Image (spheres, coloured by chain):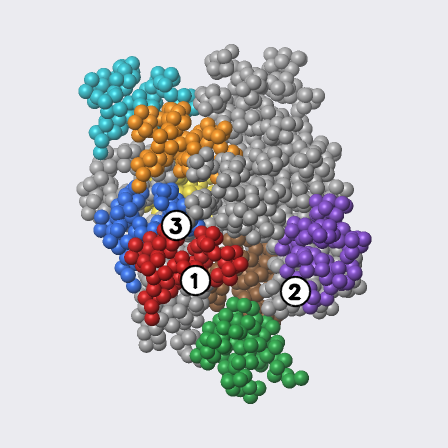
Chain colours: B brown, E blue, G red, H yellow, I orange, L cyan, M green, R purple
Amino acid sequence: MDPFLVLLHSVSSSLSSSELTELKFLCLGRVGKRKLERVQSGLDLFSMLLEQNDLEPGHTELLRELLASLRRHDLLRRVDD
Amino acid sequence: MDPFLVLLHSVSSSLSSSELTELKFLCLGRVGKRKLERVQSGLDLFSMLLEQNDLEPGHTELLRELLASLRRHDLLRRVDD
Amino acid sequence: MDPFLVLLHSVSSSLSSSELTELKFLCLGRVGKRKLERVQSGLDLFSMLLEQNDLEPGHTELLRELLASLRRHDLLRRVDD
Amino acid sequence: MDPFLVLLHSVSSSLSSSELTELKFLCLGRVGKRKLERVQSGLDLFSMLLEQNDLEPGHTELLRELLASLRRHDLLRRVDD
Amino acid sequence: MDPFLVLLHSVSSSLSSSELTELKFLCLGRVGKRKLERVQSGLDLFSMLLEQNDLEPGHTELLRELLASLRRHDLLRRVDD
Amino acid sequence: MDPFLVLLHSVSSSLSSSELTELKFLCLGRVGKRKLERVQSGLDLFSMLLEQNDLEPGHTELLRELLASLRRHDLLRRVDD
Amino acid sequence: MDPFLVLLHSVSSSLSSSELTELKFLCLGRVGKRKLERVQSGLDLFSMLLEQNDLEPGHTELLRELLASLRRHDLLRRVDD
Amino acid sequence: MDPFLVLLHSVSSSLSSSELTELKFLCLGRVGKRKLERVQSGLDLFSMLLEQNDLEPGHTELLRELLASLRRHDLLRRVDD
Amino acid sequence: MDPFLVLLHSVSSSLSSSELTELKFLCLGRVGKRKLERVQSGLDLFSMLLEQNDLEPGHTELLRELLASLRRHDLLRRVDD
Amino acid sequence: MDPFLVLLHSVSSSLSSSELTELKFLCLGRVGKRKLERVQSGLDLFSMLLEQNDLEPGHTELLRELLASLRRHDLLRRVDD
Amino acid sequence: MDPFLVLLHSVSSSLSSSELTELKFLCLGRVGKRKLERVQSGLDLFSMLLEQNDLEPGHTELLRELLASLRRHDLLRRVDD
Amino acid sequence: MDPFLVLLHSVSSSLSSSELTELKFLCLGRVGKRKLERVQSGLDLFSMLLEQNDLEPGHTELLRELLASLRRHDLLRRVDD
Amino acid sequence: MDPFLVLLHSVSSSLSSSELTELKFLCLGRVGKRKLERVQSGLDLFSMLLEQNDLEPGHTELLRELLASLRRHDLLRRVDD
Amino acid sequence: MDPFLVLLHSVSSSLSSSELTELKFLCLGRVGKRKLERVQSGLDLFSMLLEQNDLEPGHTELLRELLASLRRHDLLRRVDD
Amino acid sequence: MDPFLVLLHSVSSSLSSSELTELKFLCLGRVGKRKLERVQSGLDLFSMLLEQNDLEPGHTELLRELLASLRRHDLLRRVDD
Amino acid sequence: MDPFLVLLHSVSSSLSSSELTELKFLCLGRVGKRKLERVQSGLDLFSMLLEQNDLEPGHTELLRELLASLRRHDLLRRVDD
Amino acid sequence: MDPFLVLLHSVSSSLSSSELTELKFLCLGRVGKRKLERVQSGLDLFSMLLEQNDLEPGHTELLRELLASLRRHDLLRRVDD
Amino acid sequence: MDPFLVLLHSVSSSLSSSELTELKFLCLGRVGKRKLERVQSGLDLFSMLLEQNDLEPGHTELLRELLASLRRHDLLRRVDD
């Protein structure tokens, strides 16, 4: 298994419904409304970000900034930030 | 590639399920019920409007009127309206 | 576009979930239970009323009566009543 | 072309899957099961009714009453009712 | 058209999803599971009961008692009960 | 419109949450618990009573008796009681 | 025109594709696989049964048993059973 | 922003709980009990009056009467009375 | 119809959402999670128990003790207890 | 008519789509993928097992173990197990 | 990330339920009732305002007026006003 | 109506908040804490006692004992005690 | 190479199965059923219409009106309509 | 049935909303936030702990100390402490 | 279980409504208003301080400061101060 | 029957829709998106893993790590881990 | 083997049903409707584009543009874009 | 009986319709379109590869390569790869 996938799964397991709505709002400029309507967990949003080359194992800045905006520093400890 | 098709794809990417239902309702007089039942995205509706000569690169006032009724002025910005 | 459909869309845009519930209740004698279960917005109800000849541009007394029972005189203003 | 055939085509254009299933159910006594299993549109049903002399330009009562049972008075306006 | 088929259509029109589920549950001993998984409306169930000689214009007792178990006396008034 | 449905809607418009709870309690022997759990307004209860033949335009003593137990004589005035 | 042939034709007109597959399965021990592969309607199967002396105007027991296994009692009324 | 909405908001911000109960009592004949039970601020009552065409930017007599009955002349200075 | 099926239907009619959740919890050892996630009413649970030979007209002890654990003795009176 | 064929037909009439997929999965080591792709009912799978001498009137162990894996003990009562 | 989106998120995180209700009341003339019924946070209202071209990164007058009506000058310091 | 339910409603209408608290305390050994927390009126407690077979038209000694501990002899006169 | 044959080929290239079915239905009075059952593309129908002198480079009205009935105005632009 | 499951049901029956909140708080390190947001009763938490191998009929120490921290010794008597 | 979570639970047990209000007031600069409006016990505040990395088993200074400002030295004895 | 197939079936019967979606997310790097879109149960995913030599009776490490990531230790007891 | 064909197969393996629908829509001006109806996977579309000289090993700008419009940059990395 | 032909038959028996389509796509450069259109099973493709000297008992690199591109390592075990 990729450690990147396990890290994404662990991050997704620590996010609630309100946090998911906030993350969807903060991703409005990168993911279209039609695609955003189908997102029911952090895994789907991470998949769309992976497809758009906005999120990679070596490209994690956007995820860190999303987590900082949500004020989840405990989750940022997982990304080692 | 035709910029007209790219514009139509972009417009269809910004629309949700309720907006698609509203668009289907407002087109009841131009498209039959049998043809309207098969539409699952804005692309199918735009293609049918193209076939019936209701929508061309020089014929866009029906699309602008529909987008105005949907109260989506950001989407009218893409059509330069 | 037909002004009749624009008017119906505008009327449906001003109605809430409870108002839709009382609209469905007051139409129990004209629309069957099987068809009434599939209605999620006023657009579907208006389309069924159009299909059964209960609602036409020259046939609006049923709609005016339903809006009167809902005690929505601002909505009757749109129909000029 | 025959305006009878054009009228039949126009009627078949304004029908959905559910209406087709109900029309098939209400014609069980006149068409066999083997022939009814091949009907995928109103056109095939109309052709089979034509073959059995149930539907002619001078013989439209069965079509009229089938449309009445489906509560499609707008469709009956095409048949002058 | 037969008044029997019209009566069956009228009865099937006044039923919702839940009543259809109960009707399927209460007919488990006469219809196999493979045939019951293909019923999406009261019309299919009525046709299946017709094939097995369980429902005729002169043989309606199973229909009346199924309607009684669902506590639909208004529906029984259609069957004159 | 049926004046019966208008009367039922008017009666339901004058009832509060506690009165709805008392009505649900007093109807425990006629409506099952599963069906009683889904009632959020007097309209649902009245429709269920209509289905079970407990309430018709010529069948109103159950409604009058229930309103009498609620000590709502102003509401009995609407039913002419 | 033989009444037996007309009866066979009428029976075959009331059987669908699935029933034909079940009938072919139930006839595996009497008709070989190579011959069964060419059967596209009940008429071919009836002809093959006629050749093997399993089906005669005075010998209708196998057909009755096949119809009873398919649970088509309405079709058994045609064979007078 | 409508000056009417701002005026309504300013009026509502100067009314307390007892004043709200008195206003609800004085509005008993115009708003039903079921709707009155959901009013938790002057804004909900004002919106309900707006729906019933009892209160408009050009129709403010009822609001002045309500404020005079509450003996709030300071609030009447806002409506210029 | 079988009195056993009617009895099961009557028992399932007097159950609410919470009791269904408790019944699902107390049957974890006999039904898998995949099959339990598809149960939306007591009828589906009863059918699943029927398939596994856990509930027959001569085999009712599991149902009796499941009802006992929910403290529904009135329901046990239907099962003669 | 073979009692074995009638038993196989009765078993097949009690199996749904999901059960058919599970049975196909459990038969992967005996029937090839190309042959498994054409199976649309339990009858085809039973015939394929019949050809490979895995299923006979005197050889019913594999069918019993398949039914036990699906946890259909009611169906095992048909095989007398 | 757009600084505009981060500013909107920070504004929304400083508004309570009562402030949300007041903001919904003050936005009655621009957003329909059906759409207003689905707003559960400031983010949804901001999204609807963004769709309508009433709120843009270069168009912040309406938001300033809304904040001034709510008397949140501390929040107006975020918009630099 | 059952006179039993009318009697229970009348008894519940004569009780105050403190009396309800004492009734809930005295029923600690028969109703669980989870179920006791949801009781807001005597009707819910009476229904729970009815379900557990603690209270029937022929089983009223528990109710009489509870009313005697509350020192409400006027309420015991309604139960004829 | 004839521009008439090239035009017919270009028209036949922009048609799907459904439009071919409607074209066959609307030509029932000019082509027999025996000849229509052998048409698998628009080219066969065009050839048959050519043989019966219904379609020539100077005789296009039937093709024009057939394309009109299918609501293909873009296709009529090829025929210069 | 398992007396383990019966014991778990009995323990969950004697818990209130506040105790469930404390139980959720004290299990933060073993269950993720996403999974804890879906727990509405002690049964959900117990099943979740069962999945992670934290609670078995031979593994009851975590439950014992969770009950101890809530100061429920009467509940510990059920687990025989 | 973690001694840290047990300590937090013990601290939250010895607090009343007024102390919770003071704790909410003194944490205004670290938690938003929307998040603070949803705190009904010290557990929620502790959880949110945990998320923002303000409180860890190795980071307890802010908790000590909050307890000191409330003049609860007995509570500081639990934190070993 | 292979014990490996029975073990896979038993594992698949204990996984819900959410667990299946997490398993699909964790298998993104090994199974392509086109193939992943057709997976509707654990059996299909297990078949795809078997085809790619990622899962064998002697090769069960990937399945163990998948189950450990889902935190199903009870399911890991089935694989003897 | 041609690396071009392996690359095309790999690209087609990463595409879903919706992405195929958008690809077919964006190719409306180069491939006819009759040829587009027969495409069930990206392989057929790529073969048609190869046939019309729209796609060659030295001619890949159309493919790169189509992948860019689909917003699949990971799929552009395979084509080295 | 040649072991090479037995191996080819066994390989062809484990392939499905989609896998055959991908095999036909990957062999576009070696087999013409006219010869590829007549292939309905892997046996025909293998025979054509045998004729063109692309596949011999000592020449199996093309077959191994094709099976590797199909990601069928279990089928590569049959060829000992």
Q: Circle 2 sits in a helix, a strand or a loop, which is it?
A: loop
Instruction: Determine crowd level at label 3: few under 14, some 14-19, many 20+ residues with C-alpha closer than 10 A.
Output: some
Taking the image as drawn, is residue I76 in sight?
Answer: yes
- The answer to whether I33 appears left or right of L16 in the picture is right
Q: Residue tagged by mark 3?
A: G69
Q: Nearer the viewer, residue H41 or I49?
A: I49
Q: Residue H37 location in percent, x, y?
A: 37, 38
Q: Circle 3 sits in a helix, a strand or a loop, which is it?
A: helix
Q: Residue G56 location in percent, x, y?
A: 36, 60
Q: Residue tagged by mark 2?
A: R38
Residue at 52% x, 74% y: name it.
M38
From this viewpoint, which residue is outermost toward the bottom?
M58
Marks 1, 2: nearer the viewer: 1
Label of residue G51 in the image: 1
Q: Nearer the viewer, residue I40 or I32?
A: I32
How far apart are the two marked residues, 1 and 2, measured between alpha carbons? Answer: 36 Å
Q: Circle 1 sits in a helix, a strand or a loop, which is it?
A: helix
The N terminus of chain I - image quarter:
top left
At label 3, the amino acid type is Ser
How far apart are the two marked residues, 1 and 3, measured between alpha carbons? Answer: 22 Å
Residue at 55% x, 79% y: name it.
M46
- The answer to whether B30 appears left or right of I5 in the picture is right
Chain of the residue under label 3: G
At label 2, the amino acid type is Arg
Same chain letter for marks 3 and 2: no
Number of labels in the image equals 3
At label 1, the amino acid type is Glu
From this viewpoint, which residue is outermost toward the front?
G53
Whether pointer 1 and pointer 2 mark residues with C-beta atoms closer than 8 Å, the reply is no
